[PDB]
Image (cartoon, rainbow, N blue to C red; front, side, top):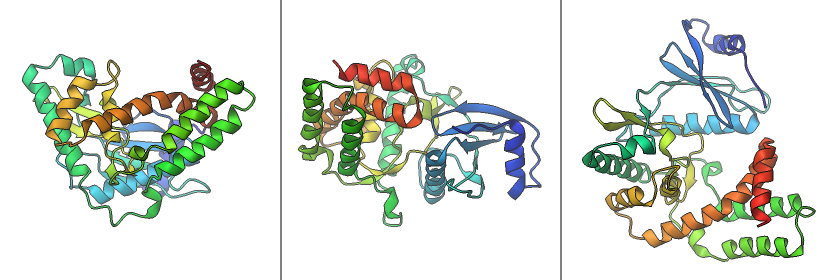
Length: 297
């Protein structure tokens, strides 16, 4: 897990952009992949904390350029891009800072009844346009092969938990994976560009107009199952919950809501294993022990 002083950041930006004057630098936020630096109150510069994080930034940069001016909500524009180094496909990238505040569920539930409806409409329209973008031009490494991802997770779980689990516990896990891999609903979808981390923190809101005014953080974007962008909003009391997302789904003209719900229910059960895996890979032992505890039950 790499970290950066303010000096390193400025020094890095200077290599390719020695004429860019930095008047103010602050840390905007930090995620699993990147540390974000707000510069001049005008740009968000993301620096990766590890190789994989650098790869996601690279994809974010690539995708945002490709879909620039294709969407009905403002999205960040890519203005600076860092050079590769060793395993990092990209040492940093600087994006336009979009104005607005996260559309928190609290803030959503406090909106007048009709503003909530508009936000549901605006989200559906965004998602519908995004899921409609022609994907022919993208390279193959952007196609999330879900069947393969479950198989790889399965191998990771069987290795990680061989000594942590007793016979019956491992059988139920293996039962879980088998069931997934034998259920075509998870793999038989029409792939499309998806945001893939479509949740309230990444939805920017204008309390002046009472309308959504931005979508951010495409670092997880990929060619995958469009239902994923609804499921990521469905978690009641944490995200928007089933009631609101059903409005979105009905503006989006979704023909199969029971499928989306089935997918949600699987993802919910599946989080325990993500926690084991990500906990192990990112080195968060609170995450690992937490999933491991949930699995033991």
